[PDB]
Image (cartoon, rainbow, N blue to C red; front, side, top):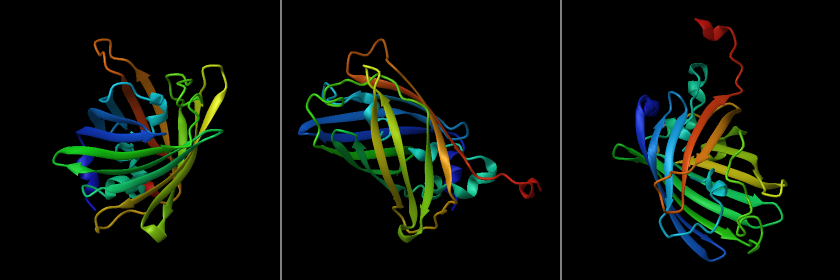
Length: 233
C-alpha cells in the first residue's frame, strides 16, 4: 500500500457531522489542514445549526487518525494511512459515566485532494441537566494515550480508552470510548502490532467569529513499539 505517500505534505481537511442527542439535532462543519510529518492538525469547527447542544470537548474525539506521526521504525503499524485513499469506517460507542452515550459512524477518506471525515452521531439517554446537556464541562481537553490493537477477524483495528473531561466544579466526567475501524476498499491494509497514540489538544476561540465554534490544534504521535537495535541498518 502506497497510501502513506498521500500524507507527506500538508493536506486539506473537511469534517462534516450531523448529530442528534436526546432529539436535540445539530450540525458541525470543520475545515483546516493536517501535517502528518509533524502529527499536527489545525481545524476550526462551526455549529452551522446555531447553538451546539453538547459541550465542544465531548465531540473532540469524534471530529482523523491518518494524520498521526508514526516514527520511521513504526511505519509498518500505521493502519490508518494504509487504508487510503479509499478510507476506513470509524465507529464508536462513547459511554458517559452516570449519563448517556454517543454512537458514531464516520467515513474517513479522500475526496479529491481533501481528506474528509463525515460523521453521523446519535446520543441517547442523557440527563437534560447532566454535565453534557447541561453544559457543565470546562473548555479544554487533557492529554491522553489510546492503545491500538489489531482486529484481524475484521481486517482492522480496535481501541478502548477513557477520556476524562474536567467538570466545572472540579469533578471529572468519564467518557468511555469503544472504537472499531475497518477499511472501505479491498486493497491491502497494515494490521499493527499493539501500540498507542499520544494526543495533545489545545482548544481556543476565534475573536472575529460570532457563531458557536471551536478552534482546535492537536498533535497525535504513535509510540509504544520497542525500537530495538536491528532497525539501525
